[PDB]
Image (cartoon, rainbow, N blue to C red; front, side, top):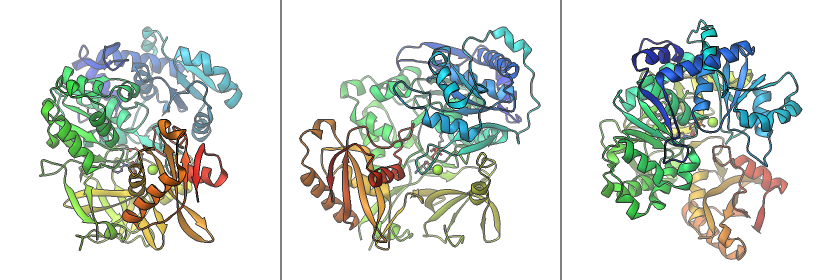
Length: 567
Ligand SMILES: CCCCCCCCCCCCCCCC(=O)OP(=O)(O)OC[C@H]1O[C@@H](n2cnc3c(N)ncnc32)[C@H](O)[C@@H]1O
Ligand SMILES: [Mg+2]
């Protein structure tokens, strides 16, 4: 299984050894099973979608995948890998909504094809002719006869061949196209396994969106790499009823499931004690947390709320990675059983220094140990010099899981993927600030979002966290801290969402004073402005990640749903 150069060779091996073993079982409601596929059935569907793609002239071309969460997406993705089509996964179009995001990906990828369901094709095909022209082909893959796979021409695949374009969320700018090779998929899959240590006997459940990151290389490809059964449900099922995630873990004895930090909080806040009494989570040995700052308070609250249900905090597996690194770089608590946490000086962090406080203290959770034969270095963003111990700098990654570059973006590719430091070359600039401590990599935040006000460095998420809890009328997770230029000097602007219940009876001055008071105590900062926005109006990615730069653009252009303003 570890001699496989690509996932096409690998699934074909699994379709022989475990043909009748169930690979994916989809619960459309997060409760009852709706559909399933065996390794043999997944292989056959893949050869058939492949043959449909090759006859449709898609080989060597880029194809958008537009599918609802389900097994059709999975089959279309593996069909593209079998066919030699560069797949471009994306969130599907939704009703009463624009296709701007989708057209922008089509223009960037120079895609000639959209792969979708019969239902969506009948609703979007003419809109795609309007936007992309007649030479663009919206194809449906859900009604391909399985006998078509007899006409599949196996491409001569090498690991250096490009498999798919993984587009970034667009939190810091425009989505960029990550060129993920076949070797990138195989190398990182092994890296996830050197850390997760899963076996053919491991069970998995995943509500994560299948389009990108943890949902695709981990929720779809890792089950196939390890030869295990994965239970899958739509993210909306978990979001509406978080108990469905933990009930599935209990029901199928799931060993390995995980999600971003916010999901652990929602499970803790929205699961009743009667529901906790229906749970047995002793089966959960790896509970991963990635794609978002891991907060120490969230780890403790989950461990405390669910210890009666058998959850152990030793199961928490902190992990870090990005699309430019395929998926994972660091993970695990090392020789420790519990996620390593350091208590350091707040003002020190604002000064790129990690030191004890002698000064308010901050608690930082490690994002894991560098997994495998990859090399992580902490470098100064401007001087391109390697930071010493206790210094905070840009995380730099050199390894075989580093993507080939950004699609049709040559200048940015040389800048971010040709990182030179001292006598070293070939490093990827992650754009993430952090530091090395205890063999563990800690992450402080994103460079492009870092706020520099009054000669001090301020992390936007640290300020957003203070504002959300300042008044009950503020919606948590729906706020942005941005720097605007006032007379040549940088100042702080807060764009925060008000709660739907508090929108009509909102005391702008009272809540603004609660906000100014909290930011001054914790950050010694005075907001130039506080813009209160309507519930659900914050510029967000398709994932839900806040676009802070677009909040500053909208404040400066007046495009926000303003229900209140302070200046
Ligand atoms: C059968 C068993 C199943 C197997 C499952 C395996 C799956 C587990 C591996 C997930 C490893 C995590 C990667 C996430 C990718 C992504 O997140 O994709 P991407 O959209 O490119 O965002 C990138 C930016 O997210 C921010 N970020 C990511 N990790 C952060 C952190 N630990 N702490 C703070 N910030 C963080 C950061 O800023 C980063 O650069
Ligand atoms: Mg990024």
